Length: 128
Ligand SMILES: [Mg+2]
Image: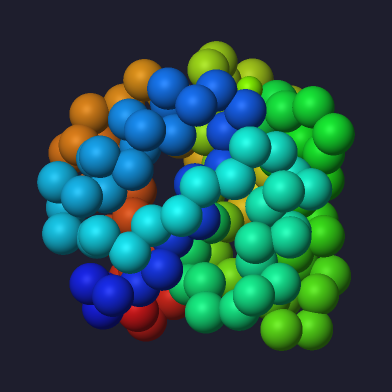
């Protein structure tokens, strides 16, 4: 994928945002911004230019599933890739995420190799 691809990393835990941003740096993606919940995320996305979202599942104000649904219903962002991150895999959340249009779902903490693999599989099915 274009290494200038602009990511938005969404998590209420500033520490995890830092970690994910650094994992992306380790993969050659330097163009990354952060958001602290689903509402903040939408405010940042409105500026345009974003090509990928990585979002935590449980957040106050607007959670990850609601963010995903809002993204998917939007004209401009309808096809914006969204990778959902969760502290623990729950079969019901996986289904809900998939049927709501999630591009993928990963359990944290994850290694750089795992993130790379998730992103690459998403890039490959979307032709990025
Ligand atoms: Mg959280």
